[PDB]
Image: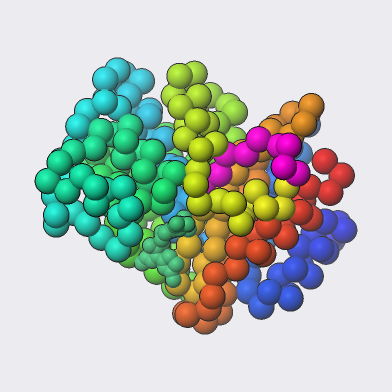
Amino acid sequence: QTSAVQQKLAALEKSSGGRLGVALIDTADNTQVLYRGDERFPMCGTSKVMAAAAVLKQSETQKQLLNQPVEIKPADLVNYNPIAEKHVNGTMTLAELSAAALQYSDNTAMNKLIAQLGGPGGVTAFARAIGDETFRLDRTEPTLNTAIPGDPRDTTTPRAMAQTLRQLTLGHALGETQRAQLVTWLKGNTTGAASIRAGLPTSWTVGDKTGSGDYGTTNDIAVIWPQGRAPLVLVTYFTQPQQNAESRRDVLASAARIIAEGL
Ligand SMILES: CO/N=C(\C(=O)N[C@@H]1C(=O)N2C(C(=O)O)=C(COC(C)=O)CS[C@H]12)c1csc(N)n1
């Protein structure tokens, strides 16, 4: 059985020619609205939230960890390095790497976060530790974005990622200081203007992390503070049948617009 919300999302999906996954959590009453909420989708860059959060968790017992400089070698650079390329044969702190990964989608920065955690398995272990039984990170940048049909690697479900994002940014999966830091980073994201943000009222405060990959994979996960009511969490994942499909950030904006009706 479907609601009018789900019917609108299905119609959007059909018009788009792809596969759409949505999960909304309204923290006013803890209700969820889902569309393909339990199907796996390639996370691409939305996985960077879990990596940054894992490092924040480490820093709860290692107080200066975020300020630890990490060397950036020429050989570290991968396919998209807008911030890390400015520090070749130099350093970035784990805070700087987190900010670059989250706010500029820097892939070299993500690889340093992954390395700090002992590899992709270290990111997954953190996910399990905070109760996310679904998330899996298998690869480093750039190959974690291959978004191949049927490939379970580097996937999660909209429901799991929404629950996790809620716990990380509004709940207490992190310490109070670390939760606030993650919120600060997400709020300052530079890559999200055309995605979930474009489908929500401009007066609402939004923190988000985008992701993109092959098969026209176009993703965004967001924590949302509407005008005068409890915050929301929204995950929008989208992927398409053919490898070189174009990005469709407009589909994410449209999904957000649909979800926001009556909120
Ligand atoms: C093998 O890796 N392939 C990638 C890829 O690096 N995706 C990553 C991801 O998620 N990113 C985001 C992202 O956050 O969406 C942006 C966006 O950065 C900015 C400036 O908005 C830059 S690319 C990076 C890719 C991306 S699209 C396509 N066919 N492939």
* Residue 202 shown in magenta: yes
Decide if residue 222 is on the left or right side of residue 145.
right
Q: Position of residue 241 (x, y in %)?
A: 56, 79
Residue 241, above or below 144: below
* Nearer the observer, 20 or 247: 247
Quadrant location, ligand no. 1: bottom left
Q: Quadrant of the N terminus?
A: bottom right
Decide if residue 111 is on the left or right side of residue 39.
left
Residue at left 29%, top 17%?
A: 63
Residue at left 50%, top 51%?
A: 191
Residue at left 44%, top 44%?
A: 103
Q: Position of residue 86 (x, y in %)?
A: 24, 47
Decide if residue 195 is on the left or right side of residue 107.
right
In this view, the residue farthest toward the front is: 86
Q: Position of residue 199 (x, y in %)?
A: 72, 53
Residue at left 24%, top 37%?
A: 92
Q: Quadrant of the C terminus?
A: top right
* Residue 168 shown in magenta: no
Residue 133 visible in rendering: no
Within the image, what quadrant is residue 227 found in? top right
Please count the marks in the image.
0
Within the image, what quadrant is residue 157 found in? bottom right
Q: How is the image coloured?
A: rainbow
Q: Which residues are magenta?
A: 201-209
Residue 98, above or below 228: below
Residue 13 visible in rendering: yes
Q: Position of residue 144 (x, y in %)?
A: 36, 61
